[PDB]
Length: 103
Length: 103
Length: 113
Length: 113
Ligand SMILES: Cc1[nH]nc(N)c1-c1ccccc1
Ligand SMILES: Cc1[nH]nc(N)c1-c1ccccc1
Ligand SMILES: [Ca+2]
Ligand SMILES: [Ca+2]
Ligand SMILES: [Ca+2]
Ligand SMILES: [Ca+2]
Image (cartoon, rainbow over all chains, first blue to last red; front, side, top):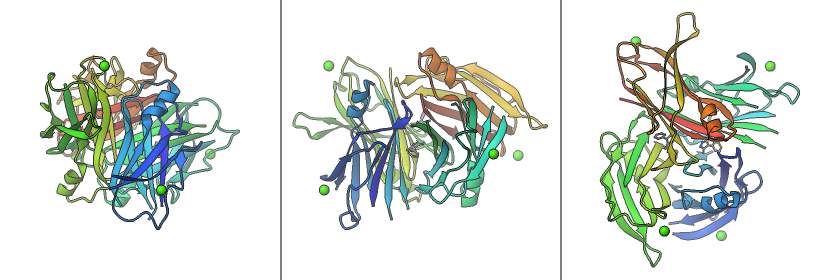
C-alpha cells in the first residue's frame, strides 16, 4: 500500500541505499533503505496502514555525504493525510521536490 | 533505450493518454501516448537511438484541457544530449519539473 | 537573514496569506518555537527574525499548505511543506527558502548568500 | 512585463550570467527572435521587453543551461531549460518565469500578475 521512490537530480540516477523512515501521528513504525532502482517496497501492510496522518522522512544528508556532495537539508520529510500510495522524491543538494501518486 | 514517465501533481495520479513526441536534431522520429501508469515504452530501438541531441515534447496543454484544468504552457519539452534513459516529468498547470534517469 | 517565498503552481500566482512557522532544535532535542508569520500579497514573508536572534542551530520551517489549499476550496494531500537545515554554521548567512505548491506535490529550494 | 529568474539547486545560489533567449511565433509558424539577455548577480533578468513590444502571441523562453553548467566545469544533461506559453491573450499581464537548475533536471514555473 505504500512505496517510496527516490531520484538523484545531480547524477541522473536512482538514489540508492537511502534510509527512509515512516511515522504515524510521531510514532515510528516502518523504515527501510532504497534498492538499486531507488525504490523501497514492503514498508507496511494493508492491515497496518490505516487512515491518519503520516510522515515519510528521507535521510538525504547521509546520502549526499556518501557521494561527497555538500547538502543543505537535514532530510526531506513528507507529511500527509491518508488505494496505493507512492511517495516520489527528486533530490538535489539545496532543493527537493516530492509528489504523491495515489492509484 | 528510452522511456518517458509523466505524473500529475494536481490530481496525484499518473498522467494518462498524454501525447509525447521525440525529435532528433528537428526531425520527428518517435511518438506515442502514455499508458495507465503514465509511462510510454517502445518509442525507439537500441539501433535507432544514436548519440546526438534530442527533444522530447510532451503535449501538456491537451492533457490539462481534457481534465478541464486551465494550463499555462503550450507543452513541456525536454532537450538533451545522449545506458537506458528515462525522462520523467511532473506536471502542474503553471509549472513542470523534469529529470533524467540514466542507468 | 531569513525569508520565505511561496508560489502556487495551479494558479500561477504568489501564495498569499500562507502561515509559516519556524522552530529551532533545543538542547534537549525538542523543537522550540522560533518565529512565525504570514506571506504577503507577493507571496513573501520578510521580518521573521533578526541577525541577533538567528544563531547557529538546526531550524525547521513549516509552511501551512493545508490551510492554504482548504481556503481555496481544495482538499490537498500534504499537511505542510518544509525544510529542516543547519543554519549559520560558518558564520551568518542570508537564507531564502522558496516553495512551489500543488495539491499533491511541492518543491522547495534554498538560496544562501 | 517579462522577467526571468534562475536558481542553482547544487550550489544554493542565484544562477548568474545565464543567457536567456526569447522568441515569438511568427505568422508562417517559424520562431522570430524577440529579446535576449543575461541574468544578473541576483539571478534575475529584467528589461527584456516593453509593454509596447510584448504583444499577444506564443513565446519561447530558452535558458542556456548548458553553458552555465560547462562554465562551472560540469557536463550537464539538458541543452537548455524552457517555457513555451501564450502571452497576453486577455490583455497585458506581467509574467515571471522562474527556473531551478540541476545537472540532470530542471523545473520551471510561471507567475502571472
Ligand atoms: C520529475 C519529478 N520532479 N519531482 C518529482 N518528484 C519527479 C518525479 C520523481 C519520480 C518519478 C517521476 C517524477
Ligand atoms: C521552489 C521552486 N521549485 N521550482 C521552481 N522553479 C522554484 C522556484 C524557482 C525560482 C524562484 C522561485 C521558486
Ligand atoms: Ca514496523
Ligand atoms: Ca519512428
Ligand atoms: Ca560553527
Ligand atoms: Ca486575444
